[PDB]
Image: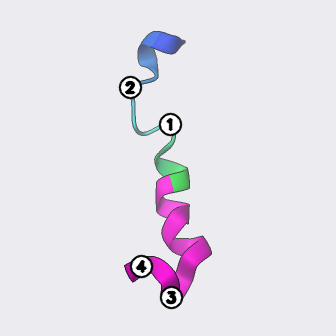
């Protein structure tokens, strides 16, 4: 489990969604 935690693909969804939740605030 913890040895595979470096696979950014697990938490990549929250990164892609960060642009969706902000919409217009994406530029900061």
Q: Name the element at disc 3.
A: helix
Q: Give the Cα distance between marks 1 and 2.
A: 9 Å
- Marks 1 and 4, the one that precedes in the sequence: 1
Say which residue label 4 marks: 28
Does the magenta portion include 22?
yes
The residue most toward the bottom is 24
Q: Give the Cα distance between marks 3 and 2.
A: 30 Å
Q: Name the element at disc 2.
A: loop
Picture coordinates of residue 1 (x, y %)? 54, 12
The answer to whether the residue labelled 1 contacts the one labelled 3, judged by CB atoms less than 8 Å apart, is: no
Picture coordinates of residue 21 (x, y %)? 61, 72
Query: In front of the other: label 4 or label 2?
Result: 4
Q: Which mark is residue 6?
A: 2
Query: In front of the other: label 1 or label 4?
Result: 4
Q: Name the element at disc 1.
A: loop
Q: Which mark is residue 27?
A: none
Taking the spot 42% from the left edge, 79% from the top edge, the residue there is 28
Query: In front of the other: label 1 or label 2?
Result: 2
The answer to whether the residue labelled 4 contacts the one labelled 3, judged by CB atoms less than 8 Å apart, is: no
Query: In front of the other: label 1 or label 3?
Result: 3
Taking the spot 50% from the left edge, 83% from the top edge, the residue there is 25
- Marks 3 and 2, the one that precedes in the sequence: 2
Does the magenta portion include 19?
yes
Say which residue label 1 marks: 10
Q: Which residues are magenta?
A: 15-28
Q: Name the element at disc 4.
A: loop
Taking the spot 47% from the left edge, 61% from the top edge, the residue there is 16
Q: Give the Cα distance between marks 4 and 3.
A: 9 Å
Q: Which mark is residue 24?
A: 3
Viewer-proximal residue among 28 and 19 = 28
């Amino acid at each position: 489990k913890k040895k595979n935690w470096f696979d950014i693909t697990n938490w990549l969804w929250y990164i892609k969604l960060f642009i969706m939740i902000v919409g217009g605030l994406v530029k900061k």
